[PDB]
Length: 335
Ligand SMILES: C[C@@H]1CN(C(=O)N2CCC[C@H](C(=O)Nc3ccc(Cl)c(F)c3)C2)C[C@H](C)N1C
Ligand SMILES: *[C@@H]1O[C@H](CO)[C@@H](O)[C@H](O)[C@H]1NC(C)=O
Ligand SMILES: *[C@@H]1O[C@H](CO)[C@@H](O)[C@H](O)[C@H]1NC(C)=O
Ligand SMILES: *[C@@H]1O[C@H](CO)[C@@H](O)[C@H](O)[C@H]1NC(C)=O
Ligand SMILES: *[C@@H]1O[C@H](CO)[C@@H](O)[C@H](O)[C@H]1NC(C)=O
Ligand SMILES: *[C@@H]1O[C@H](CO)[C@@H](O)[C@H](O)[C@H]1NC(C)=O
Ligand SMILES: *[C@@H]1O[C@H](CO)[C@@H](O)[C@H](O)[C@H]1NC(C)=O
Ligand SMILES: *[C@@H]1O[C@H](CO)[C@@H](O)[C@H](O)[C@H]1NC(C)=O
Ligand SMILES: *[C@@H]1O[C@H](CO)[C@@H](O)[C@H](O)[C@H]1NC(C)=O
Ligand SMILES: *[C@@H]1O[C@H](CO)[C@@H](O)[C@H](O)[C@H]1NC(C)=O
Ligand SMILES: *[C@@H]1O[C@H](CO)[C@@H](O)[C@H](O)[C@H]1NC(C)=O
Ligand SMILES: [Cl-]
Image 1: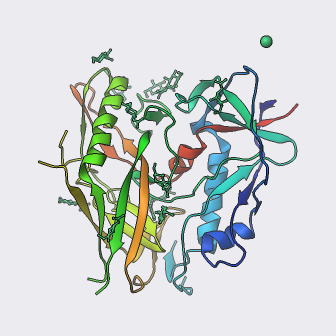
Image 2 (image 1 turned 45 degrees about the vertical axis):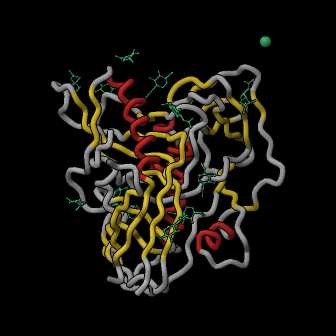
């Protein structure tokens, strides 16, 4: 093989009858999953990949952009008025497959950080059931670390680049908007479970920073979407204040940590650049049961001449959410 890139295609397990809109777009944009797909570990052939220079991330990105533009349509989009009926919405696993001529190579070593030489390399024709979850700060409904928690970064020293933390435990949030404000919402997280995981996070993160005294803090400057944990639940965008996770120390607090949320009608687009307003949340209890499997953080710019390094959660670029699950695939050209 040789390093090359070709516009791949997708594969879904969707249903042709459901009107949940992830299915709808995937049914008429992807083919059925390969019934019998097979992996083959190349006998001691070692290959090196790197996510931050992967093209399927960019290509997958373009997919969900076009998907949402087809799907989540706004009443008004300042980037034009349209129709905005409230629809069903729930992530579906999506696979990606090379066309005739190329093959995806996947890394199987449990300690891989996503940059450098993998030894246990195998060959696939399609990816795995990647769930395209759009969310900020923390990583939702993603994979799971096959060993220790892993810190993924294009360049640890460069602080303008984002840092992804892949958790080996799936700590969990439980967000709800009960019925008769119509926009009051709240997520509940087990305090000691997430804090036992984060006290591990800082200790398996200090090791990359010369045993410098690490420390966590809340976002310093932003536009809600980056400062507040923003995601989509049952078609509604949820802005949730996560100051109780990176500030409520405990590194008298082992109960259910409860964070507040608001349902924002106006949303600064994650796809292009601009605002887009919708309509009120539909009546009835709106509950989503999601898994935190990772977090996105941004280092300090300036904490050089210090004994510390404060970390703040990262947002904006949704490519890193795509990178998090695509950290193990690289498309190669068979020759
Ligand atoms: C061209 C630029 C433009 N962007 C941008 O200006 N912002 C600032 C306002 C908020 C954007 C954002 O993430 N929004 C968001 C919406 C829904 C949900 Cl559910 C979510 F989780 C997040 C990020 C996007 C960026 C990728 N791109 C580089
Ligand atoms: C390489 O990864 C595959 C996938 O699980 C599996 O055979 C095993 O973990 C590794 N193989 C060897 C020989 O260690
Ligand atoms: C996760 O990885 C950390 C290493 O930082 C380890 O201490 C911990 O026991 C691991 N947990 C699980 C459930 O594997
Ligand atoms: C990733 O692993 C490679 C090879 O083991 C190493 O050179 C590199 O420093 C690691 N990167 C991070 C961010 O740990
Ligand atoms: C990482 O960032 C530092 C500081 O900007 C720079 O000196 C270094 O060359 C970068 N690494 C790479 C591989 O470019
Ligand atoms: C959440 O995590 C648990 C344990 O890691 C797993 O069994 C479950 O399938 C996950 N849920 C989703 C929706 O991924
Ligand atoms: C999630 O929160 C709601 C509201 O507090 C609660 O009724 C539900 O039982 C919670 N989920 C679980 C699995 O306990
Ligand atoms: C940090 O301290 C631990 C002591 O538990 C030691 O094992 C490790 O080598 C130290 N690493 C650095 C980078 O100072
Ligand atoms: C989150 O709540 C804290 C109070 O606990 C508040 O100081 C902070 O401003 C809130 N976050 C945002 C983005 O307003
Ligand atoms: C995560 O998966 C669960 C289980 O299917 C689902 O209920 C929840 O809505 C998902 N979270 C998001 C943000 O889509
Ligand atoms: C200070 O930070 C810059 C980039 O933020 C980096 O290039 C430089 O090496 C740092 N200095 C020290 C002493 O770490
Ligand atoms: Cl041999």
